[PDB]
Length: 304
Length: 301
Ligand SMILES: *C(=O)[C@H](C[C@@H]1CCNC1=O)NC(=O)[C@H](CC1CCCCC1)NC(=O)c1cc2ccccc2[nH]1
Ligand SMILES: O=C[C@H](C[C@@H]1CCNC1=O)NC(=O)[C@H](CC1CCCCC1)NC(=O)c1cc2ccccc2[nH]1
Image 1 (cartoon, helix red, strand yellow):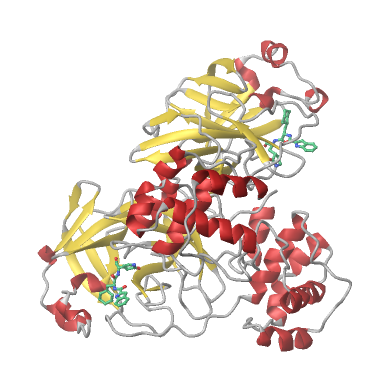
Image 2 (cartoon, rainbow over the protein chains, first blue to last red; image 1 turned 90 degrees about the vertical axis):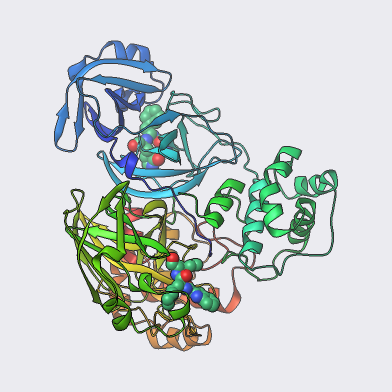
């Protein structure tokens, strides 16, 4: 099999990216049917970013203040409104490339693909996880705002993320497609701290299963443990609590490998207390936590 | 900025992927214009896998033995031929979604995106490098063959890889779109040893520049070294030799950081001799070698 950070194919999403300009600022927009979704901070001027009032700022705009370009074709804005931190720009043309889609809000620990965009043009795709502190470790440069994160279920594109800003620590913060920030962040250029991050334990375990599925077994041991005994050690290493739901989600991986979840927990416990001693798992010398159980299954099962 | 294993957006290639069925074997094809490209071992029976004579196998086939499906639309094969290890199926319909494309053969150390596909249907995109041993550390499962590796410049897709097989060590082998295998491998179910893989030094240095550009500088040192001095140490750690060309290719990154290439080499040499010692660079506890200088400049600019 082999194991790689694998994103969803980005084709269905590249067909929705447009460029949105308001005044001097240009950022990406998401064009679904006759609505373009973009960060509401496009309506902000540099003399306004420290504490904008977006209702004030949006009342002073007309439709002709928004230039929306789909490639070379300019879309005429017919209406606009604000839903939380996203601006919705109603345009006179529905997107012929609109895929089956939904807006979903993901949970910390969950992964998604990010189609990084500039001037409405897709430039790269990578896999991300919503960190426990509700930040993402993305790769974004100036102009990336409005790039979206998404998962694909068969033909359905589940948009879960729109990029708004970079925190001073260099991680990234954004909203779901309903404009609601992940985590306690606000769209103001103010001091904003991401809380302390933690390791997504269930994903480390999923990744350890993927290692066994792929023949890296050196870290396995004859020992088991209880959930509660494992979680006592997990807390010391800044690892998220492991719940019975996590154990139950790891079942299919447990079944394919014949290794009990609590047995894998005892292996992780020993990895944490002893380290890898310079050894590698799946080509990494640290415990990877940005693979969910479903990620592992799909890459080890061939889902299309 | 942030740093991530980033692949090219894959839509332009998704529009070219098809299912190719010959007998009992189903794998993926690349449909550009009126031609469908796929691995030739699609014509192999399980019995003929150990020692196939593809010229014999293809002579005994007709156009109607090749079932090409684009979505649920069946494509009619009008002609077939073999160019080395790839089969070229002429179909009666030119792909409407055909991008601007070229076929290119990449060098060791260069990277590309892989659109893993099953039954013609794109399932995932990831970044790869052509290792020095001409193998790729891929993620593929049964039905992956025909999956293509590619780079996108402007609107042009440069196809550089087509998936053919997994070596017993679990790395992967394949050909360019002209059917020439990368490395000394052949499409026969025989014992085939990939050579000793080595680390792509020029890419490790590029990634160390990415790291500096992203504020990770703990590994930097006041020391400098000559290319020949560095190479004496590189050899001992299974690292590729570094050339003045590599030095020159790393110029842009050296410029944007103000760190001389041979200064960064002095950092790498110390990282090799002492190790990271529990420290991390760009979220990695390993020196990463799958980012070319161009990858780094594109992601960091
Ligand atoms: C959108 O295109 C960019 C995305 C940033 C740019 C660089 N890397 C990214 O992820 N968004 C911004 O630049 C925001 C714009 C603000 C407008 C007003 C509402 C909040 C967002 N600014 C930042 O992301 C930003 C400014 C800043 C200053 C000092 C430290 C950190 C910091 N982050
Ligand atoms: O879809 C095509 C697959 C891709 C494989 C499948 C699993 N992971 C991959 O990358 N190719 C294959 O399955 C090809 C089949 C083809 C037949 C004719 C001669 C050339 C090879 N076979 C192989 O890769 C293979 C690996 C291997 C390891 C040990 C012993 C025999 C082996 N065979």
